Image 1 (cartoon, rainbow, N blue to C red):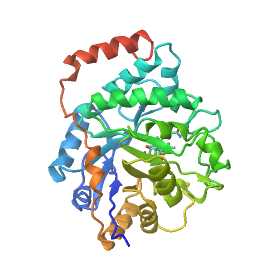
Image 2 (cartoon, rainbow, N blue to C red):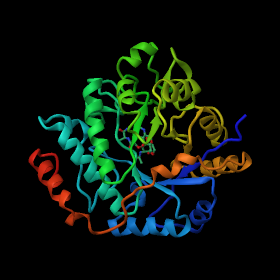
Image 3 (cartoon, rainbow, N blue to C red):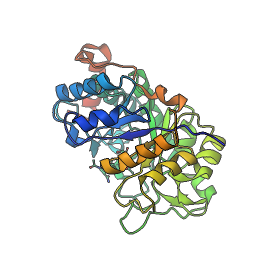
Image 4 (tube, helix red, strand yellow):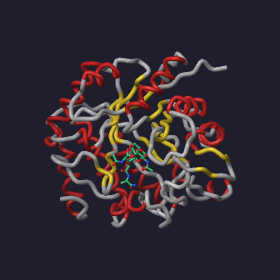
Length: 335
Ligand SMILES: CC(=O)N[C@H]1[C@@H]2OC[C@@H](O2)[C@@H](O)[C@@H]1O[C@H](C)C(=O)N[C@@H](C)C(N)=O
Ligand SMILES: CC(=O)N[C@@H]1[C@@H](O)[C@H](O)[C@@H](CO)O[C@H]1O
């Protein structure tokens, strides 16, 4: 029996660290922090927030949701990025996708963060309100082609890639408040479609994040809690070797019985490496208490998500910066 490994990613209330923020960040079972709009004012201030955090924990993973389109936390002082769907609508989509990934990842690391939780490998079936323009395409193979180019872009900029939402949010409704959404199709239907982008890119992705979706013909549990999904299918059949983040263990509408302590245990037992407790500090502290009781140690592979860029004010003098700008301005994808 495994004396398990695992880690907690949490968040803070404001634009600078309170005393409780600093004390909770000191605990080694805490491995990450994700920022949101309420933490973000101007670029100089995000850089100071990140430096503040590194003064406490030089090893912490710092994350943000910076996709483009309708999901872009870093806005003021940043290039407004296109929705994934608009990228696909060009003759030269592959080159523009690579340019977008590179530009997003260099701007994100220029303010002190390691990673963006991107790209979305979900498929636009015109069915899930949480996908929509966040997906590249509805055709599986073209979505995998354009997302693979997006990932090449992030890598050249020095940033690890997190595909989501495994094994695909496209066919199931958009996590209503009445029930966990379901994708009722057979495993072979899913393998034939929504699983394809994850299958193509399993060798290039550094990390993955599951969908909060039950696929009852495969497992009665949401994918982020299923050993069949994460172990047998993802690590076994698709030979994925990277980091597994859980979904938001404290999300509104979760429909999971048990407090955050049993959920992070469940996430870790299923095969996740790091548990996300967003927007709920009281739950974050319960999940931390739980990791302490289990004497978890950090997953070995977690340091591979650290950014290889650095905090600077320099990148705009880099040669490639101006090509990305020109190419994307030509496609009317940015201004
Ligand atoms: C910060 C915010 O407004 N929302 C956060 C909050 O934090 C984690 C969880 O909920 C996450 O699902 C969500 O972020 C996601 C990326 C989000 O904003 N999606 C919206 C745009 C949607 N439904 O299309
Ligand atoms: C379907 C969906 O939007 N899932 C989001 C994911 O994109 C985001 O990276 C994460 C952290 O904020 O929170 C999840 O709830």
